[PDB]
Image (cartoon, rainbow, N blue to C red; front, side):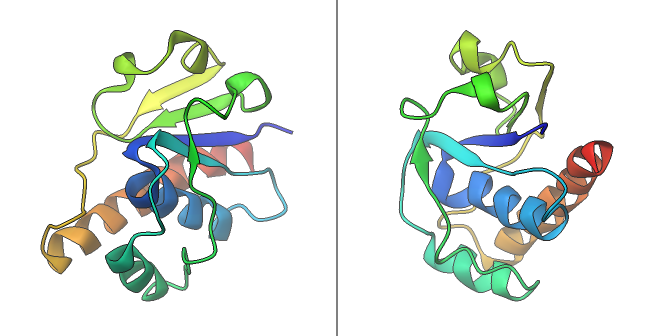
Length: 131
């Protein structure tokens, strides 16, 4: 199985936003996963904006980058335009990419939906190559 890991500064925001889309675009094909620099709570505005597209994140994992290990997850995506700042062991997997995203915590709901449109676009492109 080619398992996936989404990596952000907030696991709660972009990694969870990509996790929920990669789950609803890839369930039973491969396993999706989300990690990040801050193992923060299920984000209150993301639980809203993701339920609008059928994606409840309120029960979803928010694991820290130092508890996870990339050895089981051969597809590791960065969600910040910053992926070279991650630990090199979490970079040297067969697929490593960055989606160039902005943190939606405390932005307007139009921007919070805009980064949802961006993760949808880039999740499809990622998960559909291993489907």
